[PDB]
Length: 279
Length: 280
Image 1: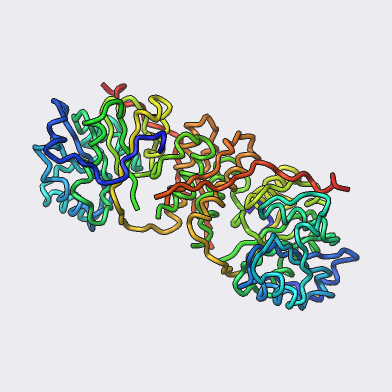
Image 2: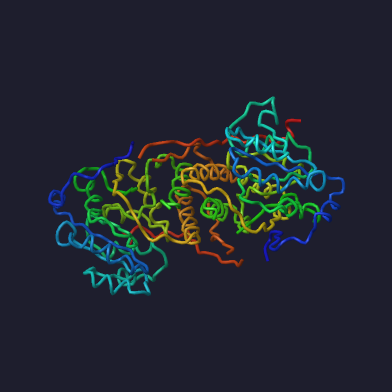
């Protein structure tokens, strides 16, 4: 009923069937983490039984955590890669997008899966449900997830998409941190800084390959640490900055100011280049 | 701040303000669509100013189907429907439409707008707003700020303004439903449809008169009917549409679609009403 390949109910494929359809292709799973000690262990544990089987590689991309994120991740048997270790030749910039970009240099899988580490009790079939359309179907190179309340999603991302890219209006969770894509697509696209990375990869994939290369899959219900409104303001600002860039609209580059005292949050207009150029 | 900003409770008294009017009249307009639960409290906070500082107080009924009108009448307020405000012109849906038509239903040199979904508003709202207009000079538009917490404001309006109109970054509540302005300014500006009217009047006033003509005043704390996220999504879409329009950016005109799992599409409008002057 939608111009977008959409799996509404729990996918039929089994872990056995999916591993067969791989056909020589490898699968890397990346968990981006910045101070996520309370939830990181549950996330890793839900994925690690797939290692050496369906999943060939599982790493945690530590974005400079100061809490017990690393030591707990190690204690769960996961390989922990810092931003520095992922790409030592290049100095580190702040932001989520930076970590996700660098993670491409720390993995070698033909298919890369991204899962947020702030998930509260994630289902162990998340990764299989994501690589589904990539392994079975053809033409698909990007699989987004949807669930369930996403204030930035429902008030900023989706209304802005409706205004400037109405073709992507059928995407339920454009800012979803849970998605999978081929290395071919990811290393060919630029990576938006900060929280712009999700909405940036979506629009850029659409512009390059059209809706036919994009699929979305239901993962049920999601629970995560709900953030204070001020953090969401900065997050929203970066989403707007990235989205405007992809639509040929000049952004002021001026960070969002909040007041009763004044503080200004950083915003970045600088994308990282496609990972291919770092060959 | 480069914007005339009153941070603490204004010093003026009802007596002083009423004096500084100098022949000028003041109209207060309450736009209302199904607000029976809160309309009475709002009117009551203003009605003691009637025949004094406030010369005119009307409720602009935007087609309410509940007991909004009868409760408003029982509170001594004049109730004007969209049809009655301007009978020559057929009625369009939306808040902006009502606010536009209200200019034809009032005769004050200064027009004050107050949302009727306020939960127990302070009775000094109207005096605190007409302050900079009556005493100071150069000011023709006074916005309010206060204290959820303005989810559409903090996630959509203010970040979008920072991106496309950073000069207006000093406005704390650009989507504030509580503001006052001169009839000259209001009748000279176009009116954005739906919930776009607030952000539209701000940017249009800025473009025409600059920051010097705009002031903002602290009103303390505000409480109003908290709406479901789906309504705010549609609200955000209209705010975006209006804001993009004022920045020379083509809007798709496609309404926001939501999947709650069935599909429903909310209306969006790119059609402004012309300045009220053209209806002279």
